[PDB]
Amino acid sequence: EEIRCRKYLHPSSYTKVIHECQQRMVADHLQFLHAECHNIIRQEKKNDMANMYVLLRAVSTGLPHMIQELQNHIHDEGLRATSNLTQENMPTLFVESVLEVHGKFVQLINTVLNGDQHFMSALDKALTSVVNYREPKSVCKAPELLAKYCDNLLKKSAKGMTENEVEDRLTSFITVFKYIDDKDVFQKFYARMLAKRLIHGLSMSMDSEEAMINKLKQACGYEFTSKLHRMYTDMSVSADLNNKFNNFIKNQDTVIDLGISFQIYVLQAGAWPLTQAPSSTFAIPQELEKSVQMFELFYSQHFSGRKLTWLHYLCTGEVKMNYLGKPYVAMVTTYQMAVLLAFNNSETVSYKELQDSTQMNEKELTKTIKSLLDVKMINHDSEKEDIDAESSFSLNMNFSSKRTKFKITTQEMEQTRSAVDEDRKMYLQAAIVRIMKARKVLRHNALIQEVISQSRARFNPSISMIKKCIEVLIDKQYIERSQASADEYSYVA
Amino acid sequence: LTQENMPTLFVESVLEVHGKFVQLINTVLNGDQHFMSALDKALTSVVNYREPKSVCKAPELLAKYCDNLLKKSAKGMTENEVEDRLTSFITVFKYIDDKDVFQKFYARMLAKRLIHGLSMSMDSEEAMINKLKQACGYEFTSKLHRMYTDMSVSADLNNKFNNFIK
Amino acid sequence: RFEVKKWNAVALWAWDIVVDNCAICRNHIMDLCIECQANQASATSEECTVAWGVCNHAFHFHCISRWLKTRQVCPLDNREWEFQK
Amino acid sequence: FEVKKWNAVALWAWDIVVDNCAICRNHIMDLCIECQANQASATSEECTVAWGVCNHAFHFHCISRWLKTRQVCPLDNREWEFQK
Amino acid sequence: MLIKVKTLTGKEIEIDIEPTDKVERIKERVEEKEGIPPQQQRLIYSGKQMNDEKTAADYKILGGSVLHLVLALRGG
Ligand SMILES: [Zn+2]
Ligand SMILES: [Zn+2]
Ligand SMILES: [Zn+2]
Ligand SMILES: [Zn+2]
Ligand SMILES: [Zn+2]
Ligand SMILES: [Zn+2]
């Protein structure tokens, strides 16, 4: 009709003939097309959705039903891709599933559907529903999952994640982050697992932390990352603060040696989510008294008008042993150091006696003594299973550790990652052979989809390790490759 | 830009630039996230353009544009069209990089747009506050929402006071 | 002889002449409540834990309990009260 | 003249709380504590609230005396820029 | 009752089965979190493998415990 009207009409009628043709061929059968909207969208008929959109755009009310159908289809695909997931790889799998849905459907909209703005708005309105979807009578999960995803992507892990790749990962993560209904809850979590990730030196790089903060400084207001930024500007300055403190040591007035490295982490009060100690009054051990009392002077002169509050439940000390043979150094908090102070001069230390040296109430004293006896550096002198006010303790001299700087519960990231990745390969063996019981013959490329579909609610498997693990099934005499067809596989059972 | 209609024309211009290039990104270049990131950086620099030794005009311009869209205007703009503009407006507001000043201006010209009755419709402010609460967190629109809430109660409050006279 | 080697101590700094207070009692937030400084100081005491909510405001537990007697909202921003940090 | 209606507006705040210039810890609407002393010489006209970008309110004398020896807002460690 | 059954790398399996729940499908729920299908996780109940119904009272009705499971394939 376009060619015919071009051939036999004045140009003023080049748009009324096609308009009146669509009103007698598309707009007159609009219900018949809207009934097929369901089948054309749910089955992802890519060749036909283009014709659907081209026909419906011309007529007046054709588009909104297709917009609603695509929104419903994206909503159901988001729920289907985020219905059931593992409780261990929950953050990364959820974020990557949402990004996969978003990328697939934005490609579909921008290729098949000419990238119409209303279809993109439907995509956004459906992804908003699926991302912060909450079970009834329960709290929404999206903020904590995305905060843990940021934690995992910014932790000093052994995944071989390069700086450029993690920058790309965060820039792609902002796409799902913009769908969070309550980002003030995500910042509550992300500023809390940025306290731990960045007061323990656990951040893999002090530049990716700034990049992630600045990716929320522009995805939200500046006040959003106002406490997130006052932490990052507390640890960058703290490196200068330690140097200034060791130079105040060089004031050259008297001898001001401490015997402790004392690598301080002075932080701002309101910015850090670290609650000031609401209980557990503490007495500084006699070795740290000099460091505390001289850093008080240094922070009195060089920064006048401030009042340090001296958190003690995130401190960390390295204390050697009492000449018990094969000396070790323990990475313990100051809570687990005052109990080792009165423990020095007296081998037999009563619960009452350490109250004059540790001064800490029994609320967390039992907790820290239990944490000590979990690895058993100290033991109950009596036979009492619990800890009472009249208990006694002495050294568990029979205790030994494989490390001089042995860890205490508050290069292991490589070993843990391999063990976690081993369960992925182990499950892949526990996924291939089920097909061998189903059809007994599968092709080389078709087995990838069956394994992935078997692990959709689980980790995303690597294509290389599918081939690598299926070769382990060969020399195990489980399955074998036929010489006639490399794709076809046979097994002994 | 025409100084009389700078806000709306500026927002439409940057929005259509974004739309044209995002169409060019994935219909031609397969829509790589790298190229979309390049588009995001480029348009962030575009919207945040300021003459040296002069404050950026973008927060004030977008606040003025959103106030104009939400204003009780005689142009006869329907609620569906203004809602579509606001849905498309966030594609520009995302790039501001100085949203802490935009809320200062938006709240400053929402105070005028609420007491004087200059609002297009009371349920259209919730179509904008919830489009900034969802896009910038609740603490962003914690004073915008408490300015709107005092309107949904005041009339009722008046109905709790006039009867108090009777 | 137990000897320490390094101490990775942490410390929050606050302005000395800017004092945070529980907005209801107007006493020091780490200090006792106004009711804990007049009535239950001798009797029980040692139970004026600093209440925290989604509002992210610091209140004495006794003060916020006396505030929640007849009205629910937080007495600094009129937000809803959840007392869940 | 006579009036049929007037549309009054009214800010409402709790009396238990008060906005305070935390440097002086006195009332924002009242006079700053440094002009409470030697009040005879001070005309109290210059005692205006100096709002910064931080959305913080302080007495002009208190915030200026702070900025004379400090550089940041005394409620959050942000660089102080006067707004209104 | 939640379980803490060990695995091939010291992992945990959440059976969420009470002491009166038969191990015919109790191992399936434990292997549902791990990934294994029901009739493939030949778990060892600290000395023996559950067969047929195998009510959990047979395995001392322990709470949580640590049940090392075998990865025996082709058992479906
Ligand atoms: Zn109080
Ligand atoms: Zn009290
Ligand atoms: Zn409040
Ligand atoms: Zn003052
Ligand atoms: Zn004054
Ligand atoms: Zn401030």
Image (spheres, coloured by chain):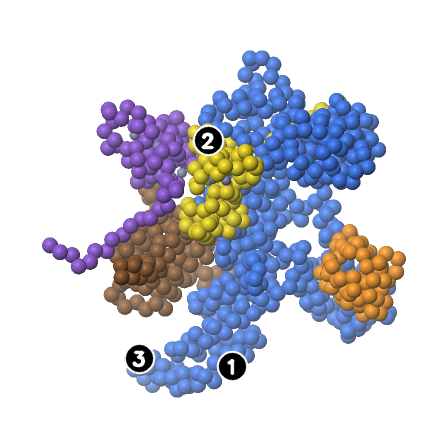
Chain colours: A blue, B brown, C yellow, D purple, E orange
Relative vertical location of residue C52 with respect to residue A324 in this rendering, above or below = below
Residue A289, percent from left and from top: 62, 23
Q: Quadrant of residue B53?
A: top left
Pinpoint the chain carrying mark 1. A
The answer as to whether callout 2 falls within 8 Å of ligand 6 is: no
Q: Which residue is mark 2?
A: C15
Q: Is residue E8 visible?
A: no
Cα separation between marks 3 and 2: 78 Å
Relative vertical location of residue A229 with respect to residue A175 in this rendering, above or below = above
Q: Is residue B154 visible?
A: yes
In front of the other: B71 or A121: B71
Tell me what residue is drawn at x 63 percent, y 20 percent. Answer: A258
Cα separation between marks 1 and 2: 68 Å
Pinpoint the chain carrying mark 2. C
Q: Which residue is mark 3?
A: A11
Q: Nearer the viewer, mark 1 or mark 2?
A: 2
Quadrant (top left, top right, bottom left, bottom right) of the N terminus of chain D: bottom left
In front of the other: A204 or C64: C64
Q: Please tell me whether mark 2 sits on a helix, a strand or a loop.
A: strand
Q: Which residue is mark 1?
A: A36
Pinpoint the chain carrying mark 3. A
Tell me the kind of residue under disc 1.
Glu
Tell me the kind of residue under disc 3.
Pro
How packed mark 3 is, by other alpha carbons closer than 10 Å (few <14, some 14-19, many 20 or more), is few
Q: Quadrant of residue A469?
A: bottom right
Q: Nearer the viewer, mark 1 or mark 3?
A: 1
Tell me the kind of residue under disc 2.
Trp
Q: Please tell me whether mark 3 sits on a helix, a strand or a loop.
A: helix
How packed mark 1 is, by other alpha carbons closer than 10 Å (few <14, some 14-19, many 20 or more), is few
In front of the other: A477 or A280: A280
Residue A439, percent from left and from top: 77, 74
